[PDB]
Image 1 (cartoon, rainbow over the protein chains, first blue to last red):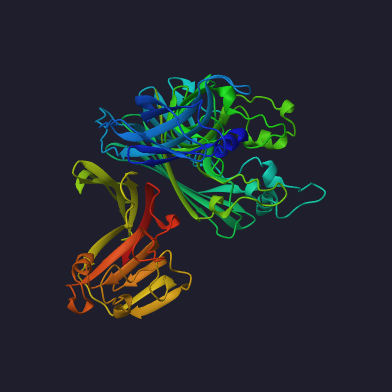
Image 2: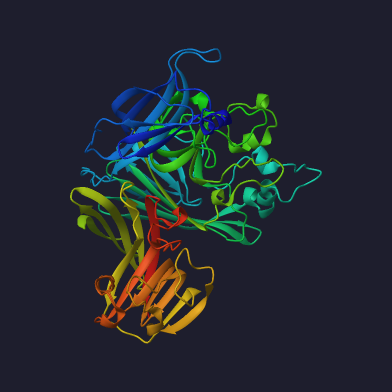
Length: 409
Length: 204
């Protein structure tokens, strides 16, 4: 997937947007843009409102101004984005006709949603047991284990939806860059992985600090607090709220605190193993290829739909992979999640990835493993034998907040 | 500001209030602010703020709250960066400790008045019987932002009725590479789109 990043950064045409005008600059030193078409397009959250085509006429090292027709100004809420692509109409000796040689995208506007969800005709119904809290609403049921403080299971009808409870995750199956040259015999203590390991990130223990349930007039509200510790040190604290309303939507709010003296964590998110297994993955966010925080310029914000298989990157030596960033809506099966996050989805758990040395040895697990990250560390790469993730991409803030909505159709 | 929602509920350990407001201007929704206030049996009020900023509006100078307190005290005590005025792009010289100054010192008498006096990375602020905790930046004085902005010379400012307090979850940098063009670097503009902050307010 890195190849795309290269392709984009190395493109020969550069763009600037000013008002309704696009300014094109050519980085060719000798040729004129004589086999180039510019396609543009405006979309609102993935929905297309307008498209166009213009042929390029730029001299090597020159500029071309492209005047855009008046753009649509939807009322509907969402993000309006402009995307341009350069196409080579005719084939060449090294390319086919219709080859895309450059692209660029811009956010034009945003209409914030000031809307209120309508009344529910009922509200969920709570039930306290000793072991759990159980909320029910129609066919839908959710259960929270009182000893772990986690959402342990959920049903739609009589069908269980999870094989594993939903929980916080702060680590990743290490990348080659996270490892560098640390060998088991000859450990390299500066390698990220060595530091995470040693701080106990990989083996910290969750401790329930608090798990309460309350009935409000419009919904049921659950509150939890957990601490992850390791040998006396509290590495992280996670405080959440789950609110289930009469519409069957569950809203989750997460606030995490990270000890300033622990190595910055690879990620801040949640995970679970879903029971279900589907064909496609559909999302509204950056894509379509795998993208990470320090490797996402080539990606575009749109609506993508791929087969599950494509959400996995078969690096010969396995590690965390497949992420997609800046996602606002994710759909898989009957589920739907909304917020602002990054995720990955596949049949391999982080643990399996991390424990299998060759791709050919991985085996698909029981359902689908989903990792939803509020934040994720960069990947680096300036070199592979020293820490190469720039500071702007390390999770060093100390306090993080994220939220999501989970629902079914 | 437009009220979108204001609910109250009784939980077992406290009372919970929830609000949502939208700020608009000529049809456009510039910002949305959603909060929760939770008052427990200990008399502490915890506030949680989540703001959304339209990506196409110019980044705002700040994201916070304000109010005019009735009280007027002598000293200001805080645990955060100080002791002098510090802003996000001007705070390396400041130190994180416990400071105590006279109210007067929390004001910077620039001949031509403007926003001033801020202190960043504050974890606890005490003034009078009040106490606030969180992670924020603030300023405190007898002049409202409106007065500062409307008075051209320092000598013309008049102390207002009580104390004006500005608690910011976030604040834009000040710049200065030059004074005749936009000089605030990008890393100091409030461009994230979504902001979250929280505090605890209590009395002694």
